[PDB]
Amino acid sequence: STGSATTTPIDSLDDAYITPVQIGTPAQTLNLDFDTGSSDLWVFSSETTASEVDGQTIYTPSKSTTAKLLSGATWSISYGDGSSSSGDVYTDTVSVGGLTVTGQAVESAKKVSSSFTEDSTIDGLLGLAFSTLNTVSPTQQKTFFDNAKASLDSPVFTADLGYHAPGTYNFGFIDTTAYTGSITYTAVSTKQGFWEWTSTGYAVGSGTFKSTSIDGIADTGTTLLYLPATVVSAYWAQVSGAKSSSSVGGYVFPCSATLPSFTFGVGSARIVIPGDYIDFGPISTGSSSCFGGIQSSAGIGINIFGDVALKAAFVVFNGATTPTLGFASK
């Protein structure tokens, strides 16, 4: 089997991407944030505290003839931005882009933190990291990909995120028309439950490539690119007037700037992030200070190749017995 679904930016800045997902019978379509940095599929639901729901589409398990309470199971998760959610669990039929999993754990939120409530466009998350990170207790549950894997034509999914445009998540096949040149594959460590890999270095603009190992995670759920402070300083030093602002919470730059590209290494290959991808617009409406798309990972504890990086590439998440990651230009 295979599946193919379009993913769409939630706003003009590509702050996140939503992908329609069918849950239950008859189908209830919710728009979920596909997140390769977590492993829970959770949704706003009929059980979510009323004051914490504001415009989201909800899953109502009582209206699904295939929903079954997973008795005794609870979940609770916190994300890298400090947001959180928790609740109980159903199993139900879940389809993505024509690919169907029966008995998928669908984690129903009873509580969500304010950032979720305040974002009307995201109805939940669909985790695509390794199932070892799944938070369901007392019986850990498998991700949608893990459940689908054996049925797929090939045990892979791909992320093809657009810059200020829709893109695609495919399951079970590699669309050879979706990228240019060849795909370069690189080793993955699953020890922390992430798609963790080691970039071979970077360049700023037309500058020389610096060969240096940068361990990090491929994380579709993260908006920005978080790298070591040394690397990030070298990038922003090439932008007149750019500075790290403690008050704003990272590097900002004059909105009048033209940003340089940023290149990262994948083995001997190179992925170029155009400068425009690194512009996240005014820090507040009408400001001439703009927020940067490359930020320091210092104090996160891990480097994160988020959407800023991934949307410059066609990315293969290879879930074979020994997982790997592939990157191609596009």
Image: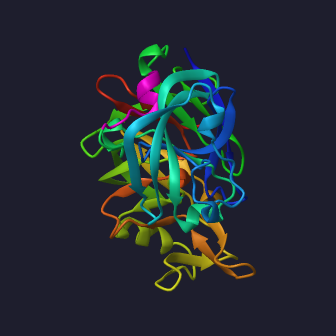
Could you say where residue 52 lies in the image, as x and y percent from the top left?
60, 63
Query: Is residue 109 or residue 249 the one in the foreground?
Result: 109
Could you say where residue 165 lies in the image, as x and y percent from the top left?
72, 46
Region of the chain picked out in magenta, as a range: 139-148
Residue at the bottom extreme, as displayed: 247
Task: For the N terminus, give its image quadrant.
Answer: top right
Left or right, residue 89 beside residue 1? left
Task: For the C terminus, give its image quadrant.
Answer: top right
Asked whether residue 209 is in view, the answer is no
Query: Is residue 33 or residue 206 the one in the foreground?
Result: 33
| Residue at 35%, 51% in the rendered image | 216
| Residue at 54%, 51% in the rendered image | 307
| Residue at 44%, 57% in the rendered image | 203
Left or right, residue 24 beside residue 126? right
Left or right, residue 243 beside residue 16? left
Q: Is residue 312 above or below residue 283?
A: above
Q: Is residue 305 above or below residue 126?
A: below
Q: Is residue 304 above or below residue 146?
A: below
The image quadrant that residue 258 belongs to is bottom right
Asked whether residue 327 is in view, the answer is yes
Could you say where residue 87 lies in the image, as x and y percent from the top left?
46, 51
Question: Total number of numbered labels?
Answer: 0
Q: Magenta includes 143?
A: yes
Q: Magenta includes 159?
A: no
| Residue at 60%, 44% in the rendered image | 32
What's the coloring here?
rainbow
Residue at the left extreme, as displayed: 191
Could you say where residue 305 lies in the image, as x and y percent from the top left?
44, 52
